[PDB]
Amino acid sequence: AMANSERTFIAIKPDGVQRGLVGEIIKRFEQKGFRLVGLKFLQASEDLLKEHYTDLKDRPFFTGLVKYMHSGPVVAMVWEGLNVVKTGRVMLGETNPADSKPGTIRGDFCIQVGRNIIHGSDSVKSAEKEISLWFQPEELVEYKSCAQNWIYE
Amino acid sequence: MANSERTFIAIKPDGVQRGLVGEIIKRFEQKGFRLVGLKFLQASEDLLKEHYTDLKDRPFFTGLVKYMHSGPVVAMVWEGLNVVKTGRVMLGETNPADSKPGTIRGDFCIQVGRNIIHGSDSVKSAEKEISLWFQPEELVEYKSCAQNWIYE
Amino acid sequence: MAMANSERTFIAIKPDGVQRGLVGEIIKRFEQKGFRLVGLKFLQASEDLLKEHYTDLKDRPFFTGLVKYMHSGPVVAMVWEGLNVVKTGRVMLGETNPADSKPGTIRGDFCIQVGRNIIHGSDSVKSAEKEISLWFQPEELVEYKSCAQNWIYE
Amino acid sequence: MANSERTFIAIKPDGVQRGLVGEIIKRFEQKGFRLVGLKFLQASEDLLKEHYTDLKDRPFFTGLVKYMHSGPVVAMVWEGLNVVKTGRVMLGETNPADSKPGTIRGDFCIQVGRNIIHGSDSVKSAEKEISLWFQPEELVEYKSCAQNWIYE
Amino acid sequence: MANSERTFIAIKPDGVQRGLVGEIIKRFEQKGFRLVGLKFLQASEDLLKEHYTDLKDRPFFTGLVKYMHSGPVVAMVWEGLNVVKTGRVMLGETNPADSKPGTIRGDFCIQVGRNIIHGSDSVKSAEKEISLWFQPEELVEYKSCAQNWIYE
Amino acid sequence: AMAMANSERTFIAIKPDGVQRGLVGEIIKRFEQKGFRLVGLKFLQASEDLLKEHYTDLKDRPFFTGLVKYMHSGPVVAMVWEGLNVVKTGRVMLGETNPADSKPGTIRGDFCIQVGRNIIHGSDSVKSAEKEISLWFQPEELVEYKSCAQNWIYE
């Protein structure tokens, strides 16, 4: 119930993996001071993706999104820290890469909406839902970062 | 074809002198834009008076043409979806004082007369600046191996 | 080239900045921006120094915990010089509150919480002159001409 | 094929703690090797004793297992021509004292007990370590978009 | 003048395709070498066949030319003290298997047929390769603002 | 505290060409990311007398007078770094004294070219390092603290 232990779901999409951005993206979260809790590599099924993007069932791009997210492996991640959901999105940049600012992950590394390299949860509620959807509870590891007292007061 | 749009980017003589050529090209590559043209030359004053012809009546114009002739520049053509507008965002505000950190100008320079880089401000200007600095046979068209992961 | 280009600001890397190994990365950003380094030292600031440094915050509820924490480890104190370096230096640092710091800034990229914002920079020219005189003796500020001066300033 | 060789790379608990996961993964990506498996776990002691089974009688074995159990690791499988041998070169000498600048250990660590990373020393060891740390359901095979530009 | 030695560096089609152009130029800039020529082109097969004329009897020659012609390349001239020999050191062993981490091929490529870059092996070869790839009009000479901090 | 070998110190000086070419942050970052601990740091124009004492073993060599004049000609970053075998490993990190022999990935291998502009100096021995540290720094300028990752750097 601690603010500093909030968690978010970050997924590196198949274009991110294919273009070699996995380390660069993870690096950005480490240097910010957030803590890695969950990490895995899989080719997501369409049933998983249909559940993940369930709020978009009725959008013309939903079919192409589900099937594109299936077309290659993704990196699934859970990161933990104070306001990690909100600050994650800031670090990611705007969902539509056209408006992402240089310095953000999307603003620095991608161009088009169908190919926006990354996803991050839009709310603490979406996060807990997405974490449970992609991770099993035993796949989430907690540890104390040696630099915790220098990240948090 | 929206994905084939081109913009002219020029690394100005201070950008070449301060060692920023690779860093600037690296940013356009890692963004996903595709290099089409690349040369290194000391631009002539006639070329520069035509490049900055809209500034002909401004009090800084003669100094701009003269300074831009004082060293070699790196002339580039980049291709991609909305590469003109997005390229300008990557460059930062023309005035380095208002450039945001993360942009080329925000990270790498300070003052307006030494703003290290230029990019076309419109599709119409890009087409003119490309034809002004590059000959058609100097612009190379190839398919990036990541084309299907950059564009849907 | 002008003496407006001689403006100076005080930048201090806080104990969290030193502990988390950001000293080089921070100095790099000022170097690659074109600012010139004028003073650089490494010390554990005394409480008298810190209280005088944050004299304007003497009546703030976080003052005692700010002064003790800044004393709890060593800091890197720097003086940088350049046109509008005070204002531009605050832009590079990002918002004082890390939550509002944009990506691309020092705080937006490297820290999370207000008590641990890794870096301080003078907020005005008057603050800078008072802070530089507070942390650096005149003999510890070195002036030299950058080989790139003529390509940074017109 | 030869280009489908695989090695097991594990980022030890000190590399996770010191914020090295991204940097390490970047070096394998930019080298051109392909990521096949990736997980984050706290290895059990039983797994670690089988992983280091050739060291049962070394005076550091018990402390090595205990240290490798003290915190989570990142476990990885990478694929490519000679990834086992080249992987070890990238890592640097097992003892960081001897690792050259430019390697992971040469750049990032100091002491043998805290050498941030492990990589299989042979194709035999790799296959054994991959089977030990990964199940078939965790190994993803995809075709990199740059394959024909990394390989003949 | 010894500090005026020049070498020819070519970023091969795989280096362009995998987005390494900026990273490579950066390494030469930060070392303190000076860019003298820079161009982007698709090399004709006649040019490539003369460039590699010493290799025409090797079994790999036909496929080397095809690979070197399969996409555009970035051709470059770089000037500095012992730039021919030191460029090779920076590039790494021609065979990427032998290249050390910290070199260009050591950090970025794997296989002999896709080794991302070429540098002249001698001053004599350099003068030949430069004349072959660059016309006199395409070379620039300027004083680097750091020359006196690079060279006593 | 740890074993006393973990507390060895070396003197590192970023020369005027290191400062002029914008390498200060890059150099410090390599020492930080390697695990070593920063113990002293100052910016100054060293007097020729200081430099003649620093290089006293070279006082009769043909390059000595110009090396002394050159090192005085602009400001230097003087640092003290602490860690296991930091003297020897620091020298490996810097690369060979002659830049032409310095391998890529080292400080001199990546960033410079010629003998008289080799951007950096590091102590060559423990004994040298004690002498240079005392020459360049007063003891009250050397700061002792515990690195938060010490248990992950040292066994």
Image (cartoon, coloured by chain):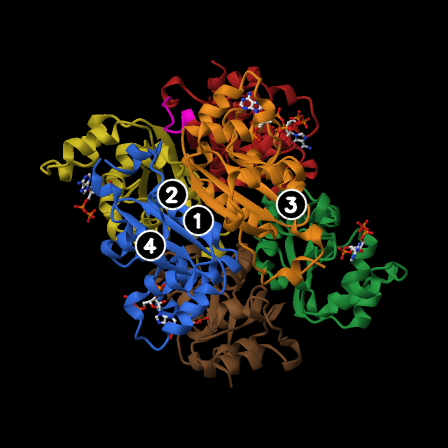
Chain colours: A brown, B yellow, C blue, D green, E red, F orange
* Residue type marked 1: Lys
The answer to whether dots 3 and 4 both sit on one chain is no
Residues under numbered marks 2 and 1 in contact, where contact means CB atoms less than 8 Å apart: yes
Which residue position holds label 4?
Answer: C134
Q: Position of residue C105 (x, y in %)?
A: 38, 58
Position of C129 with respect to A48 (left or right) is left
Which residue position holds label 3?
Answer: F86
Classify mark 2: helix, strand or loop. Answer: helix
- For the residues labelled 2 and 4, the Cα–Cα distance comes to 12 Å
- For the residues labelled 3 and 4, the Cα–Cα distance comes to 34 Å
Image: C99 above or below C25: below
Upstream in sequence: badge 1 or badge 4 = 1
* Residue type marked 2: Glu
Image: C119 above or below C152: below
Q: Quadrant of the C terminus of chain D?
A: top right
Which residue position holds label 2?
Answer: C140
- Which residue sits at x=36%, y=68%? C97
Say which of E9 and E151 sits in front.
E151
Upstream in sequence: badge 2 or badge 4 = 4
SS majority, magenta: loop
Q: Give neighbour class at mark 2: few <14, some 14-19, many 20+ (Cα, 10 Å).
A: some
- For the residues labelled 2 and 3, the Cα–Cα distance comes to 28 Å
Q: Position of residue C41 (x, y in %)?
A: 44, 49
Q: Chain of mark 4?
A: C
Upstream in sequence: badge 2 or badge 1 = 1
User: Which is closer to the viewer, label 3 or label 4?
Assistant: 4
- For the residues labelled 1 and 4, the Cα–Cα distance comes to 13 Å
Total marks drawn? 4
- For the residues labelled 2 and 1, the Cα–Cα distance comes to 9 Å
Q: Position of residue B105 (x, y in %)?
A: 32, 47
Which residue position holds label 1?
Answer: C41
Q: Give neighbour class at mark 1: few <14, some 14-19, many 20+ (Cα, 10 Å).
A: many
